[PDB]
Amino acid sequence: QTQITAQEQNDLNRASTTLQNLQKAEDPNADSGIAAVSWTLDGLNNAEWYENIGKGQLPVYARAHVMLNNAHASPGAIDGMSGKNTLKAIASFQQMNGLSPTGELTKETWDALVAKQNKPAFIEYTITDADLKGPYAQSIPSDYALQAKMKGLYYTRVSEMLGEKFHIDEAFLKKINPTATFKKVGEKIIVPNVRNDLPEDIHLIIAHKGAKQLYLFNSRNQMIASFPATIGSTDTPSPTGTYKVVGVARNPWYSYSPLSLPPGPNAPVGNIWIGLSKKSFGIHGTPNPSLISHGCIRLTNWDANDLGNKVRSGVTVKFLE
Image 1 (cartoon, rainbow, N blue to C red):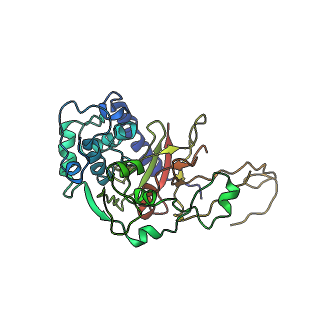
Image 2: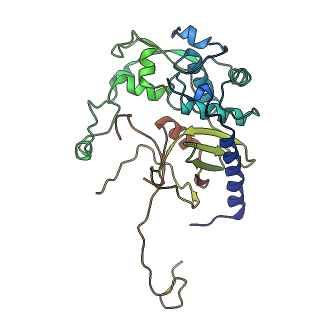
Image 3: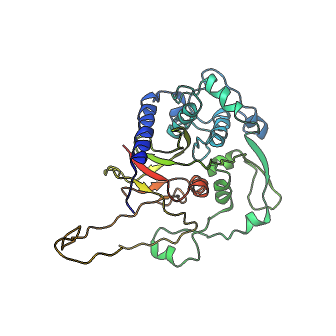
């Protein structure tokens, strides 16, 4: 119930050194890491690498985003903009593919990115009756009492549900669909052509707090998947112990609150147990950005669910500063 074969420890030590090096290789100055044209379906899908791309929100970065997400280096919410999440997702893809994990969006990197892709980055999608029906909720108040009386903390609007469905940021979805009302069945929109299907080889999971990223490795020490992550809380470091994944609970209910050996002096604990407060950690999702720890791990709702399908109860999880 608290075991840890040396192999495990070793396997984790091995992995965390790949990561510590990976971070040493990142280029903080890469244009793809800093925050600051045709946004059609054809323009998006035929975006082209070119010199001096720079920072900002460009069709080229949005094509990269989809392509990363499909190569298991998830960039998070698709944005088309440069920024930190973008940097670490290219870095992850370079590492998994034998190119220097710098995070810079080189041509060499880009060319490889497109080569793992047979499919177009974006596709045409038809808003349906199921989409318009929800169930929805008119608001999610922030007070827990108010939230508590609802039937469910549903999605609040149609474009919210569809953005989480195609891993795209909501404003970005609207930007690239400027005539969409999201109130008509049969409406046609442009969406990410995303399917991140992870391997069944998930062996160990590292939450790397410095990089703000969750990394997945297999038994051959190859890093096979990555996600942006907000790990624990600021102002307290992350747990130094090692944990195993016990269960996947989907659509959970939240809870808020403000052998057997006899006793004696020769028991394995002796005759007294001063009990310390227990902590309870999970890898979980996030709600709408407007809404909102030490050792909780926060991903986007769709990344945690992609993880939730493939991970087997048993894999070992560690933190790394």
